[PDB]
Image: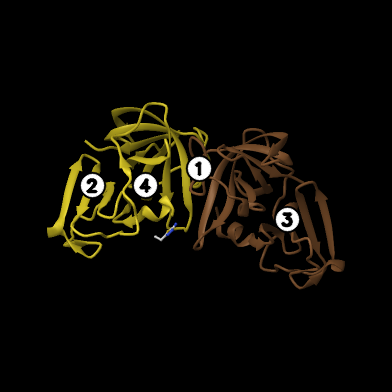
Chain colours: A brown, B yellow
Amino acid sequence: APPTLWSRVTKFGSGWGFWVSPTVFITTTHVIPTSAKEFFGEPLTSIAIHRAGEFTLFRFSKKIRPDLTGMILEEGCPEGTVCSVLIKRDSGELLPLAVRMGAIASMRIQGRLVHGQSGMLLTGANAKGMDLGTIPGDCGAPYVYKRANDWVVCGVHAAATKSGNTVVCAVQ
Amino acid sequence: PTLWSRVTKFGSGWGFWVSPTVFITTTHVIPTSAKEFFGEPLTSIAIHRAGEFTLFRFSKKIRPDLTGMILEEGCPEGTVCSVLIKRDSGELLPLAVRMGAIASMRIQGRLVHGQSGMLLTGANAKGMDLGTIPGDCGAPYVYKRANDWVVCGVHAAATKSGNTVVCAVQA
Ligand SMILES: CCc1nnc(N)s1
């Protein structure tokens, strides 16, 4: 994945989020610190929040990331699309986990109720563990895919089954 | 602990530490002019070659941080292996491979002997992060079996289009 996509992935709360443009930041609702009253030097009064279940979008009053161009945010992706989940790991390592996307789903995972676009990891027989699959600290990482002439972002990482291949992408 | 620390840049490709003293790679990536590897003179290294599979056994512990792993001659048909691709870009790319028969295959016009496989990303796999490139040779094929990771070969070749790969094996 191009370096401009990795540069958008930002350590945030108990996981990650992703800069869509200089003023727009998306993340997984449950990684947001509940006590927080300031983000990137802006008080909550200067920020518009758009939330659908595990999807949260922040719109800032001023350019926070003026080095970036706005890119395309889709509401999920077509059934059968292969995405990469852009996960940052121990020691500046970059782990773009291949995922085939499927249906909109509601599931119970580790006792929590989750809703978004389901997918299956294409990394191994089972993705149990940190070498082939996801860990809790990966939530908020972006789902991206390559088209003929550009890259699209279509959601953020919300949940994964243990001893499985199944993931849930939260979508706008 | 991580399998990824075992994947090491080597020659024109990569190799894999099975144990503190044993290193496996693809024959064609090995430098053809050398007097030492990893600070050890070639005079104290044992080299075992079988076509595109090479194993080095060192006289001293190069990676004393590691435990010894299971090394087998390929795996049963229909096993879904993972090829652990390390990239100079800074990416780690684990890809699922459904394994087939051992054969002599024509790949981009050359004969390659090893275990066939097909990527689950499929034939219309579209980009650097869904398939292999020539610099990836020597990346290990692994799978989990009964509590243990098994290494069953090293990346030797791949088709230009479609989804075929070849794992070089021992013996
Ligand atoms: C050879 C140095 C590297 N470490 N991790 C990578 N992906 S390249």
For the residue labelled by badge 2, is the local secondary structure a helix, a strand or a loop? strand
Q: Residue at x 42, y 58 (%)?
A: B88
Residue B130: mark:
1
Residue A26: mark:
3
Q: Amino acid at mark 3?
A: Ile
Vertical placement of residue B144 versus B43, above or below: above
Image side of residue A75 versus residue B142, left or right: right
**Disc 3 and disc 4 in contact, CB within 8 angstroms:** no
Vertical placement of residue A76 versus B118, above or below: below
- How many numbered markers are drawn? 4
Q: Residues within 10 Å of mark 3 (few under 14, many from 20)?
A: many
Vertical placement of residue B3 versus A104, above or below: below
The chain under label 3 reads: A
Sequence-earlier tag: 1 or 4: 1
Please identify, in this view, whether the residue under mark 3 or under mark 2 is nearer the observer. Answer: 2
The chain under label 2 reads: B
Q: Residue at x 38, y 48 (%)?
A: B136
Q: Nearer the viewer, residue A107 or B140?
A: A107
Instruction: Quickly name the residue at label 2.
Output: B55
**Residue A134: x %, y % from top left:** 57, 47
